[PDB]
Amino acid sequence: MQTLESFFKP
Amino acid sequence: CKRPRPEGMQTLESFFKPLT
Amino acid sequence: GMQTLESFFKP
Amino acid sequence: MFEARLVQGSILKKVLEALKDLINEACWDISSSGVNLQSMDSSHVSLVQLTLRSEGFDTYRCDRNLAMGVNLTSMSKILKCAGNEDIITLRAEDNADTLALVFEAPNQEKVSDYEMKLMDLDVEQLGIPEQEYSCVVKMPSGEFARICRDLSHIGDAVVISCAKDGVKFSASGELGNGNIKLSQTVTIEMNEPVQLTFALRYLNFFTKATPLSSTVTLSMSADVPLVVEYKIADMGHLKYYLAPKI
Amino acid sequence: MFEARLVQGSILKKVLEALKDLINEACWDISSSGVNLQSMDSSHVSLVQLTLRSEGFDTYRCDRNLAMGVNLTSMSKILKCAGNEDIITLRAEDNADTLALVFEAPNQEKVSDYEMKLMDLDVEQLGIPEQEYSCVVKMPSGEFARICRDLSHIGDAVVISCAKDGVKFSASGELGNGNIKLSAVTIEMNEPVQLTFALRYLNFFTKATPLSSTVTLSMSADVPLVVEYKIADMGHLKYYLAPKIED
Amino acid sequence: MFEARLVQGSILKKVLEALKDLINEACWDISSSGVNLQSMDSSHVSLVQLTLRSEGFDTYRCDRNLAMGVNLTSMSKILKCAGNEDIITLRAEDNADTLALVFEAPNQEKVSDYEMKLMDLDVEQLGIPEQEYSCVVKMPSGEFARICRDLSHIGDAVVISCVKFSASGELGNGNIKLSQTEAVTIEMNEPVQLTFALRYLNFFTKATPLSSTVTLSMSADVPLVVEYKIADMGHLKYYLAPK
């Protein structure tokens, strides 16, 4: 899997 | 080695002969 | 943090 | 080719719960008279015999005869996924290493498909002769399960003693002993009376069938295996066989 | 020969739940008068004391006083075999190496006989003078047990603090702290009292909780806490707990 | 001076049961609009976003926003001391070392007061945008739980595929087919067929008791969002990346 923050803006 | 068998009973094979 | 009941009651 | 639909899939679920803590692999015999299973456990000390007659499946078609080698453990995790009110259909291409399982439901809304592989299984069948036992004890299946649980805290072998007007159960261990005596209501039918000892570990797997029937019947004779049967209403039965102790 | 018949056996059943966990061996004193069990738990920090009055049974028979050495674990295991609605009967001979327990279904169709290898022990009984308590609380069994359950998830002892219109249980711990104020709850208090007890022991006592719907807590400055569960027109279980002390 | 009374205490208990198994620590942010929480499981494959509107609460007071460093385990432990008919109050002071939970028992009988120690904590946060999801499936929570609990025993991963859940492992495979309407709706602009970890979905579903409905939402090459709505006051959205 890929962590959720390879999909979301910080 | 001695093949494990609960203590004190016979196989059912000693009572019912298997098909063949 | 406690004490034994022999402290409080006599055998 | 075999296909078989069951309105009360409730039952299959329970059959498998019965069979599963006792044997892990077995062989399902499928014919047009129905579905039969015979298996001993891995110690060859008990044995279970399953029959689900064709005339009880709300749809039955066995095309040619068919022995399906099955991991009951796997199968058990599948039937656990069946809802209790689910209509269970079975189906098997007339060979291929794969049995199919369908769970339809109430309002035809959810449909579950599971395919389990199957297994070249070389397993060993016994011939149990036709006979009638000295003592036939009929009791409420619940009453029998708790009996075996109770005595099983006291000891690990039970002494079953049959008599005209009553049956007795006895065990003993490093704790003391104990004795349970039931007496004609719980029904007996008897030629000669009987007394054998059996191992509770196995009895206590047998009562796992208990939800299949409200009654259970044990049959006995001197120096021969116990028979423990459950009537799966309208449909067939589960016999367990247990060799006597000593 | 001793012979107690208790028609409503769910009671012997609860008494062993309520004991087996605190102590595992005890000595049942039988006599004209009734049963009497008194044991300290194993650290001596707490004590249980059971009374079952003869006039409490359905049937009672004693010809020679008896101290029976009983393994409580074993007896609860046997008792755990009884129907919630069985008539139960304790029987033993003077010979005595063996206490019988009999469970008869209310139709006289099923009947069990479990007869229990006894034991032998020396057991420090304790003198416990009748005494007044400077404050006493009645409370629902249940509410006391949740209060102790609750509080033991925060801390490991409870300050039970008493007033003429409130009891407060409080605890303290690594995750923070908590208290619960209580204004069928009744306080009869000849004077205020605040004391601190170990929640472990209390959490064993609350097990008697199925024997009664009410519990009383009796306490005074530097004398053990008493927690009493009254067994309907028959007797009681009373537990004693020494107050926590400065280390 | 934060204050939030809640006459339906249970809502909050169910909320803590829903989180405690997925995340152990978390920052509770309080503002005038109400309460919010964002946090990833330590795997970092999922997070939960909580929203409890200030209107939700029967009473609500707040003159300084607030980030409370909460140990969710010990919050769960405490909240297990609330009674389901209990009114619950959360109060915290301008300055933060502790949170305070009061459980007023219905009938003026007993009050309990629990001061929870807070932790100074640095839990990462992510910005998630308002987007259009190819599919949005709705259905009863109950059913959607059973489906994960079911396929968990078959494989450790489900392929969702508008609607069909499915899985497979050493023993074989399985799938479940839902369409139409026990109310199960769809909203579709594009076939979609992602693959998620059952381990995670099974955590999300501890939120089932808050809501008889769940909603899935998905679009290719992006995180799934599963949502339970705390009635008349907000929601609990879980997000999970695909494999």
Image (cartoon, coloured by chain):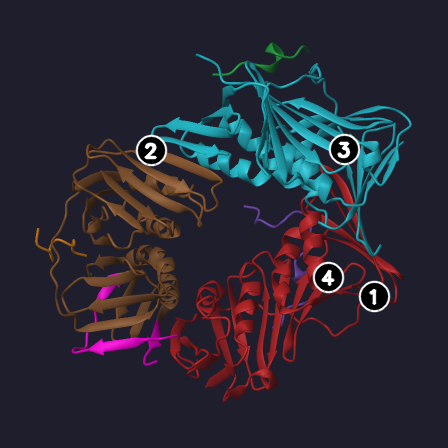
Chain colours: A orange, B purple, C green, D red, E cyan, F brown
The answer to whether residue F184 is magenta is yes
Range drawn in magenta = F175-196
Compared across the picture, whether E204 is left or right of E8 comes to left
Q: Distance between the residues labelled 4 and 1?
A: 15 Å
Report whether E117 appears left or right of B4. right
Which amino acid type is shown beneath numbered disc 3? Lys
SS state under label 3: loop
Marks 4/3: CA distance? 31 Å
Depth check, mark 3 against mark 2: the one in front is 2
> Quick one: label 3, few (<14), some, or many (20+) residues within 10 Å?
many
Q: Which residue is identified by label 3?
A: E117
The image quadrant of residue F201 is bottom left
In this rendering, the answer to whether E106 lies above or below E135 is below
Please give the chain letter of the residue carrying mark 3: E
Residue in front for this viewpoint, E108 or D239: E108
- Mark 2 on the same chain as mark 1: no
- Disc 1 packing (10 Å; few <14; some 14–19; many ≥20): many
* Marker disc for residue D188: 1
Q: Position of residue F194 (x, y in %)?
A: 21, 68
Residue topped by disc 4: D226
Q: Mark 2 lies on which chain?
A: F
Q: Is mark 4 on a helix, strand or loop?
A: strand
Where is residue E146 drawn, in percent x and y?
51, 39
* Disc 4 residue type (three-letter): Leu
Front-most of F159 and F188?
Answer: F188
Residue that badge 2 annotates: F115
> What amino acid is at disc 2?
Glu
